[PDB]
Image 1: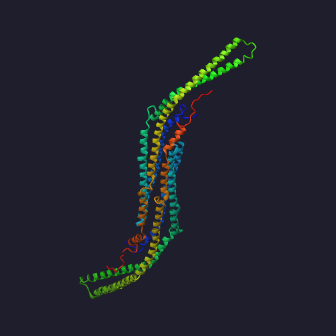
Image 2: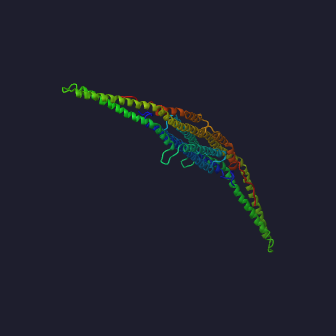
Length: 289
Length: 290
């Protein structure tokens, strides 16, 4: 069957160790690709802000409304910086934390594979070998007993089949009656040895189960570290992504609203009247020589 | 000078009308391009979420930690959705609002240009024409007076320059002393005309300023609507960009923290033990015959 207790079925547990290292890679890559997306967003906002600050300044819009318009681009620059901090945190802290953890947990061998994996497999084998030897003996004794059971059944099926032949002197009967007695004993002998090997196996099961449990718990604890670590890192990632908790993010739009509200149509119009319209001084024609 | 009150210098005001339309385009394109950046961010998050929800599920990670990991992708899907709402608001509300306002404020004429600009142009010209017409007459009367001052000074000069000529004659004296008198009375006439032209110009100045202010005031009004509109739109734009307000954004990371915390190492370990470890049932060897 597929039971863990069957010889060699500890392999799923050993394989989980290798999968642990592979999953650290996936998580690192997962965070890295997310960080890259944050950078692209930041970069495009920066270009957009730089582009339009230039287009507004070169253009015919001036006064307080120009300043209000420019506040819009300043918002993009601040949001951009914020998202670059997200990238920074994901890479310099979270990503690097997994990288260091993986480096300390998994040690690659010259011939390939991790020492941690080999240690578990060697552990299971050491615990399972004594029980596997006794199990080998039971199988052999089972064959010997089953064989003698048939050899003894084939003798009776010859003794009773001879009681039809009339030419049956007592020598031929004693021959067949002794073949049955000899086979009867060959069965009892093997039944005992086959029963003995089972008792020796049952007496080895407790130690076998204890030793396998011991190595299995080491594998569980090692896995426990990775799982709890994954839970830990993910909570730190959600911190770095969450901008709804940082005060500076709210300040961006509090300040943006303030600067936009400084837009004063009255003031802009006052200026145009005084410096471009009827408000300008004028030398009205006078008498001259 | 470059004074507004000088002929033709109303042009800067008329030009401001055209700039108004151009600035609507700039503002629309400015918002439009910002909206595109939002969409790109939303799209990349979506693909990243789709990509890794698949990689994690096909991978060897299972149990509650898998679910916690998957909550990370779900966060990106929700932020993406949130930023697509920003894009939608910027385009369907803000961008569209400017487009409709522009359509209503500026009307292109068949021969090019805007009806609004031609109105201001014609208004200024109509109000300036009668004042400029009087100004031309003044300049003409000014020259005629200055020229009379020259022709006179020449007469006085040539009169005294004959007082040093031995061949003088009471006839040529009377003749050239009369030219001095003609140029003299020719001066005061042109002086009186040049003064009268200025007096007429001074009487036409009040209406000139009144009519000029009237057209300019209308230009100020038209401009005020644009400025106040820009202030209104931008304030609606900053609302649509501000995710720090909406509770939905804060819920994304409340739920994310919540789902991650569901990760339970002990539960995952107990599972592996039961279905893959010592917990599994076992048909231990018994006695068997036949």
